[PDB]
Image (tube, rainbow, N blue to C red; front, side, top):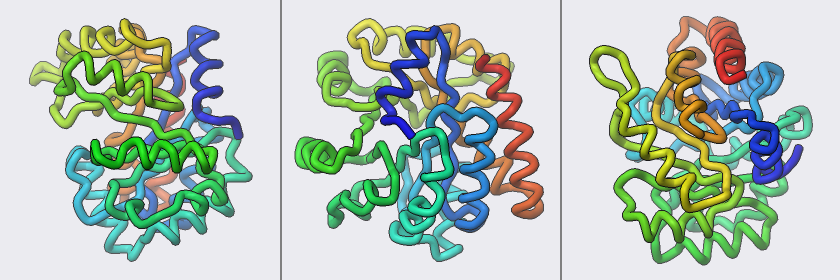
Length: 261
């Protein structure tokens, strides 16, 4: 598969918005995560974000936090996630971006994620003190360090972020952005456009949005990619069984692929 940056560039030259599913590795088990990764690919996922469970995933929404807890109770570890990727990556046509909080990786060299076929890395709580050391190490291993920005980061720092980021710029929020009459809040349109104004990099938007009309609107407001997380993790990991999870995940993902096209 291609780097994340190349995959994104190509969609943007074509006027197309990337479909970026997010699932948590190990929920409900790693054999099911493998099969999910292959199904997501076959439904036309452009990039897949894959979460490594940790004991405090405080930047994630509650659906994803509950999935992370389930993945830690299935005894899932960084090493077991890398072993699975090493088998599954050669079969996927699209790149994987690993998401992990900083403490589990603070002790790694990133040599073993590269070897396992990971292309990108997202460290949501990356320390300001460590961000350059990790960028350098990711570079030295041929991995792209994808950075978050949020509506809380002032404009001048947001610009420094966009410059340092690789693969795409990832715009997220810990705050919900849809209202009680089930509309996307209009301030989201400005939030995406503030970041597009300062960079030529692909801006991918992870705001917790799952309905096909809503996903279409985030695209139409200029996102280059839409990360669909909570709703994918629900379909897969809140089902009656792994088999039903996968059937539900495929139907949902086809519908999101259709919406975004």
